[PDB]
Image (spheres, grey):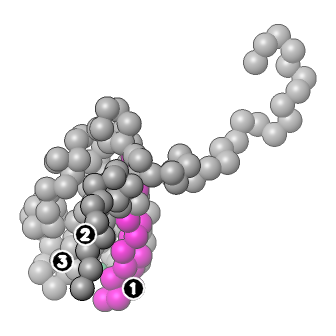
Amino acid sequence: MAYSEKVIDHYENPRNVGSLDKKDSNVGTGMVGAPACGDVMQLQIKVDDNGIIEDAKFKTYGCGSAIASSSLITEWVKGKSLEEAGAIKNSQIAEELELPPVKVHCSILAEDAIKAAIADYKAKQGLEHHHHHH
Ligand SMILES: [Zn+2]
């Protein structure tokens, strides 16, 4: 930047992960696993476009099919409202892929992920009232 062009000797490289400051308030995180296909699915939703998902990251590998489900749910919940991301349920994405039932375990994780991320995002919203007790 600026005329002077002899400084900067490391190339603008990124030094963060998939979250801004883990301060929540706009970043639902969810990491589930499926002991069946020994596959860990880590989803990451980001809200900022006015409560809308400004972006969404994914990360899963192990099964011989889920590696694709991440591409769908990712290209379907990007820039949309949480009202649509927290509704696709698992039976919907499954019908979009059309895969055997005994193999719907991966789809369940995908859905359980969008729900865990939203639930974790609202956990830091302030909707808590008198912690339950028993
Ligand atoms: Zn699987």
Please state the horizontal and vertical placement of residue 105, each as a whole percent of the image. 22, 80
**In this picture, residue 24 sits left or right of residue 49:** right
Callout 3: CB less than 8 Å from ligand 1: no
Mark toward the viewer: 3 or 2: 2
Q: As shown in the figure, which amino acid type bears the numbered disc 1?
A: Gly
Extreme-bottom residue of the structure? 36
Residue 34, magenta (yes or no)? yes
Q: Earlier in the sequence, mark 1 or mark 3?
A: 1
Mark toward the viewer: 2 or 1: 2
Q: Is residue 129 above or below residue 21?
A: below
Q: Residue at x 34, y 59 (%)?
A: 123
- Give the CA separation, mark 1 to mark 3: 14 Å
Proximity of marks 2 and 1: CB atoms separated by less than 8 Å: no
Q: Residue at x 38, y 36 (%)?
A: 48
For label 2, the SS is: helix
Q: As shown in the figure, which amino acid type bears the numbered disc 2?
A: Asp
Q: Is residue 121 above or below residue 6?
A: below
Residue labelled with disc 1: 38
Quadrant assignment for the N terminus: top right
Residue labelled with disc 3: 104
Q: Which residues are magenta?
A: 30-46
Q: Mark 2: few, some, or many residues within 10 Å (few <14, many ≥20)?
A: some
Of 108 and 129, nearer the camera is: 129
Q: Quadrant of residue 108?
A: bottom left
**In this picture, residue 15 sits left or right of residue 122:** right
- Give the CA separation, mark 2 to mark 1: 16 Å
Q: Which mark is residue 67?
A: none
Q: Is residue 89 above or below residue 104?
A: above
| Residue 79 in view, yes or no | no
Residue labelled with disc 2: 112
Of 107 and 63, nearer the camera is: 107
